[PDB]
Image (tube, rainbow over all chains, first blue to last red; front, side, top):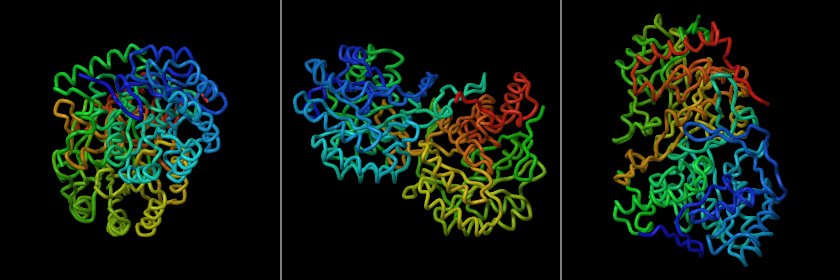
Length: 313
Length: 313
């Protein structure tokens, strides 16, 4: 039995990694991810200059997941590049960096700095077009003209294979339109589906008050809320973007949910809220549970069932 | 203590009604709704000609709600108009009809037929711009130019106050853009937030197969999945459209969720998946539970707390 994944010119021990908002902001966070049983890790979605993020409270755990409005708190791109160039142990696992500039110009400046480090160390770029928590900055992935511009300018400036993290879509026409843009950019080799369900609102009935401070309580939803949306987006892009890979993100708490993501088409599987709740020990559990499912079904490798979800029509 | 609501020229006994996909397709359904303790009821989202809808299986109950791709099965506009004109007992409660033509031309023809019945009987129109389950027909509410066209032509053809049912939005710019369109149409007096979270995907891990037949398993999500999204949309339009009412739809299983919808700004509260599960006796329970919460908080009327959700900013 093998959980190995061979993609993007790298060997991965298993398909699991963190989502780019969880356990990846500081050097200590990244050490803990590297020492875990995860197949990879991704650095916090970063900006050209450091950010402290939105005011507190900005995170609230829920029975079915979480709501947050973190606002891209990060140590600045130079920190994550220095980690990638000097600190990370690539003998343990490959490294992704999430770059989330708040304009195309900012994103271009950031990815240019990464070029030499990618060439030397193999660091992989995930361009973030999905953050729903920065006041005054709409999710880029919901504007297909703006998305085209980001992909054009990053393709030009970076010039190497990279991936994109997308917001969730909820209409078939949007899957079609999104795929039409993505398929014009051959350097986009993977698509991460999905970042949180944006701009939900949680109210505490006891005190009649919202649970987070930023944006009048409006924040991104994670956890069990996201699973069917995530599966749909993974499968939609798996079918529409045959020249690319899809990574799953949303609602993974167990090997069973991981299995479903991979069945829908996922090459890698990102863990967010469940990792926040359980800590990096979760990766050992997820490897074991996925192995158990494969053993029961008689699958020897992930390639036997990736993207092989059955339909009735 | 009172659960009464005074809107749209009527006194409603309480704020509860069905959502326009549940217990409202046939004459028997509508009789059961009328005999229930609900404050109102709405006829099935209808089309000019009858539809039998999508192939089976097209509904699947989930631990956290439901997934469906019903495909607007309905008896045709003439049936619901005849119900509104001849059958419905307006002494029990007011009646809404949901009209969901698949083109502007179809919707115009349908609303023209309603005009005399609205004038005679007081039947209220909810124009559906939200159905995520008709193959080849995107959700109108996600195209703001098309939405403008529908609202312009229905305003001209119908000429009396009406409401609209919207798909959920997930980005602040979309709340802004949607509200800007809606605020150009003074005849739009209410906004129902939200219809299902569109185009989710549920897969059974045991047989590796999707759970519904239409659209390769892609279907609208209801129930506990949708509550924070529904609350967010209710409150976003409550604040952005001060000259309009908002109705809440999504995630209501108890008086507590109803209370939250009303706090967020809802005038009426529509019950979907929970009503499908429990049947029309649910309305008696919801009335009791909402009254209990009000008694515990010392509230005498809904107007004491409607739209009074507290923020920290």
